[PDB]
Image (cartoon, rainbow, N blue to C red):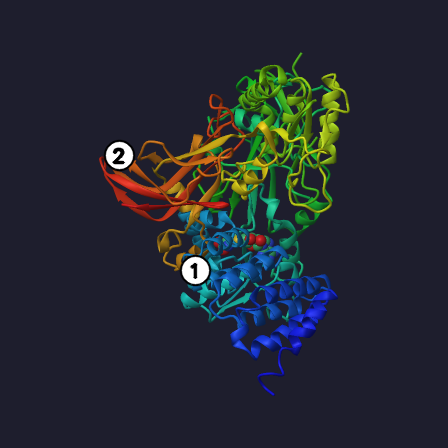
């Protein structure tokens, strides 16, 4: 009764499926599969479904506890099966368990290193886990050298017990240990960071006096974790705005619990007022008419200038597209002594304070650029000014709501400063002349005029071509652009047009209707197509009738610089909903790129060996999380050396299916001798065969991307290389051959 008496579990699991019961079905399928390897492929997909829905049931009951073990059993049943590994990793990633799905993606890649989707998902998980700026920090030789010198000077002064807050890779704890610290303790909130910090400390042979903890500093207890109050506290929990990573609260906790009567010792914040057209394009709507659509003055847009995410942006002002003008002189904003618990407490209960700065160059007030000097001690200090090429960035406070932004010689800039929520907040920015929440990409979209001009022209062309008078009931226009878009309002002016906007914000819909009224629109015209209860994007149907669409504005390019996923599938869906003459915008897309030499991209993607880290071996452990593509790039101010001519890497036709090829190859003319390190790329969107939008143009809101290489390639002027390009459904892969 071992062979026959089995699949009664299967016949009961069918009944359980009929009753929406997945636990009994999962257990029955476990019984059937673990007793019959012959059925592993017969009920593969049904078991997959059963386990997915049972895991959803378990997550609804807050039973991750056993959900992870259930997924582990599912793996145990199927050994080398990269398909199940990948699919289950995506299901774990979807439920919010990235720290756990990372291992499943790693195993899926280990079973087949050529699995496309496995690697393309592992890169997502690694980008979410390890943060990019870490790579820029470990490669800062100046930062590492100065921190090592300061920690050594502190240890030689009598500090034998050192605690590292925000240890990350544990390189600061290793600096302390190598300097001769007796007791070294480190803490890091991230699971993955603790994970590879263990590896780094072990391989560098320092697990003796370095005790690692997986917790925030605010969770440390004495003597439960560390046995005593330490004599030294090191940390690098600082950002562009210093307080952005919460050093104040952590150091208040450290002085109140874990310290004897701190590196860094102090900080002096400096600021300046800058003119910059790019910052203005990203954080201020300059134009008041958008291709014939008048924006009313009572509807004022703003960027995330908050009043709880950062109320400022971060920019590398040392390489801003175009440049920047210093309208004033570098002036002090505040000073923080990290060896002052009184001041650290008073900053929370501190009221704002005003500062006035004179103008030295007449221009346009566009932003407030803020950096700081981190005083490790009386000797060592690290600056983050744009004149210094370090790893850090500069904080940028935008300037909203002023009658005139022109400042002259003799005027001042008056501003309040406050650190009331441990976040550097500069407010009340005004100029005494001497006697909607749109994102940065949305602001730059409104500021981008050629986009709207070309869209209006192509829309008018197609609409007039579809009207019966020239073809020999109003026309329907669909806009599925992700975010704010005035394209439906533009289309509404071109005759009997029914525009549909997929914008999902209530605020944005109200604003679009107010703008329509400002343009004397019948309010019934602009209909908002936010249709769903829980759908990712506005899934594509026809209107209330099957009267097929005339114009469908798809979203093809992600503002990160990559091609937006499910593009060809959504285009194939949309092609069936067009009438005999309809159009999908864009009509096609040409992906262009070139080969360059950039040390900047190399050091942005991965760590450059023990050179930068001063002997300590950290690159092999952290470069496991390096990704092949840099996103959100401005090729306008990219520090590199071009090595070839820009060529077409890909074509993507959205009206024609059978065109968009797969494994294409391109021959590239190497027109300069050097070292290929990366492949930047951008796009040209052809709406009409005449009209073209250049995503690399300095008026575009989009960003460019770049495939960064692991090992730089040596080439000479006159050589010709080959590039293999794959458009795998929702991803683009660019590999090289000599
Ligand atoms: N109070 C705290 N306790 C533990 N980790 C913290 C923390 N505050 C911030 N962090 C984390 O520490 C990380 C900083 S890494 C900064 C230092 C760098 N890893 C080095 O040793 O050279 C951030 O990812 C942040 O999330």
Report the residue at 49% width, 50% height from top.
Answer: 134
| Horizontal relation, residue 522 to residue 114: left or right | right
Residue depth check, mark 2 versus mark 1: number of the one nearer the observer: 2
Q: Position of residue 442 (x, y in %)?
A: 61, 31
Q: Position of residue 63 (x, y in %)?
A: 69, 67
Nearer-N-terminus badge (2/1): 1
Residue in the foreground of this view, choosing between 461 and 465: 465
Q: Which residue is disc 2 drawn over?
A: 672
Mark 2: secondary structure = loop
Give the class, few, some or many, for how many residues have Cα within 10 Å of label 2's Cα (few <14, many ≥20): some
Q: Position of residue 160 (x, y in %)?
A: 51, 65
| Horizontal relation, residue 442 to residue 663: left or right | right
View extreme (right): residue: 523
Q: Quadrant of the C terminus?
A: top left
In the image, residue 124 sits, relative to residue 407, either above or below, namely: below
Give the class, few, some or many, for how many residues have Cα within 10 Å of label 1's Cα (few <14, many ≥20): some
Badge number at residue 621: 1
Q: Position of residue 466 (x, y in %)?
A: 60, 21
Report the residue at 52% width, 45% height from top.
Answer: 375
């Amino acid at each position: 009764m071992r062979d026959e008496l089995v699949s009664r579990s299967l016949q009961s699991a069918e009944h359980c499926l009929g009753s929406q019961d997945f636990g009994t079905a999962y257990a029955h399928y476990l019984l059937v599969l673990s007793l019959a390897p012959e059925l592993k492929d017969d009920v593969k997909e049904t078991f997959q479904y059963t386990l997915f829905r049972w895991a959803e049931e378990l997550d609804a009951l807050s039973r991750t506890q056993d959900l992870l073990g259930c997924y582990e059993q599912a793996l145990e049943l199927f050994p080398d099966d990269e398909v199940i590994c990948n699919s289950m990793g995506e299901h774990l990633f979807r439920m919010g368990f990235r720290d756990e799905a990372a291992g499943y993606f790693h195993k899926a890649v280990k079973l087949n290193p050529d699995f496309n989707d496995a690697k393309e998902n592992f890169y997502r998980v690694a980008n979410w886990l390890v943060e990019r700026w870490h790579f820029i920090m470990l490669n800062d030789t100046k930062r590492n050298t100065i921190y090592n010198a300061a920690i050594q000077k502190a240890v030689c002064s009598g500090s034998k017990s050192v605690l590292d807050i925000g240890a990350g890779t544990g390189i600061l704890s290793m600096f302390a240990r190598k300097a001769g610290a007796h007791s070294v303790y480190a803490c890091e909130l991230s699971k993955t960071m603790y994970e590879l910090a263990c590896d780094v400390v072990a391989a560098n042979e320092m697990e003796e006096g370095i005790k690692l903890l997986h917790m925030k500093s605010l969770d440390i207890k004495i003597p439960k974790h560390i046995p005593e109050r330490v004599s030294l506290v090191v940390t690098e929990t600082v950002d562009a705005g210093l307080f952005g990573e919460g050093i104040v609260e952590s150091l208040i906790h450290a002085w109140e619990h874990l310290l004897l009567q701190v590196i860094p010792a102090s900080a002096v914040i400096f600021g300046i007022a800058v003119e910059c057209a790019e910052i203005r394009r990203h954080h201020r709507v300059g134009v008041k008419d958008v291709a014939g659509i008048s924006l009313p003055t009572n509807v004022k847009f703003q960027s995330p200038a908050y009043s709880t995410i950062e109320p400022y942006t971060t920019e590398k002002m040392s390489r801003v597209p175009g440049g920047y003008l210093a309208l004033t002189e570098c002036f002090e904003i505040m000073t923080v002594d990290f060896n002052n618990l009184q001041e650290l407490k008073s900053l929370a209960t501190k009221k704002p304070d005003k500062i006035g700065v004179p103008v030295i160059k007449e221009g346009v007030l566009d932003a407030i650029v803020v950096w700081f000097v981190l005083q490790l001690d009386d000797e060592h200090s690290l600056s983050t000014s744009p004149s210094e090429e370090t790893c850090w960035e500069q904080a940028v406070y935008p300037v909203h709501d002023l009658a005139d932004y022109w400042i002259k010689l003799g005027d001042e800039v008056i501003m309040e400063v406050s650190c009331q929520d441990c976040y550097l907040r500069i407010q009340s920015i005004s100029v005494f002349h001497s006697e909607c929440v749109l994102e940065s990409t949305e602001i730059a979209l409104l500021n981008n005029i050629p986009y709207h001009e070309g869209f209006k022209m192509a829309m008018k062309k197609v609409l007039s071509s579809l009207t019966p008078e020239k073809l020999g009931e109003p026309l329907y226009v669909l806009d599925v652009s992700e975010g704010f878009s005035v394209l439906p309002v533009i289309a509404g002016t071109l005759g009997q047009v029914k525009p549909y906007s997929s914008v999902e914000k209530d605020q944005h819909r109200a604003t679009l209707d107010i703008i329509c009224e400002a343009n004397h629109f019948p309010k019934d015209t602009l209909e908002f197509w936010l249709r769903h209860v829980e759908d990712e994007s506005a899934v594509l149907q026809r209107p209330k009738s099957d009267k097929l669409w005339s114009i469908i504005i798809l979203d093809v390019i992600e503002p990160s610089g990559l091609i937006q996923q499910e593009i060809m599938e959504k285009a194939a869906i949309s092609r069936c909903l067009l009438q005999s003459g309809g159009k999908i915008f864009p009509q096609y897309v040409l992906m262009f790129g070139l080969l360059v030499e950039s040390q900047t991209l190399m050091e942005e993607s991965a760590v450059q060996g023990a050179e930068r880290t001063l002997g300590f071996n950290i690159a092999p452990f952290i470069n496991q999380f390096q990704v092949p593509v840099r996103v959100f790039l401005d090729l306008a101010s990219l520090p590199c050396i071009p090595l070839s001519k820009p060529v077409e890497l890909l074509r993507l036709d959205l009206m024609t299916p059978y065109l968009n090829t797969s494994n294409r190859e391109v021959k590239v003319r190497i027109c300069k001798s050097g070292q290929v390190t990366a492949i930047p790329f951008w796009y040209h969107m052809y709406l009409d065969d005449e009209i073209r939008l250049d995503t690399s143009s300095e008026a575009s809101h989009w960003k460019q991307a770049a495939v960064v290489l692991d090992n730089p390639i040596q080439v000479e002027m006159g050589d010709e290389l080959v590039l293999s390009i794959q458009h795998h459904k929702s991803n683009v892969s660019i590999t090289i051959k000599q």
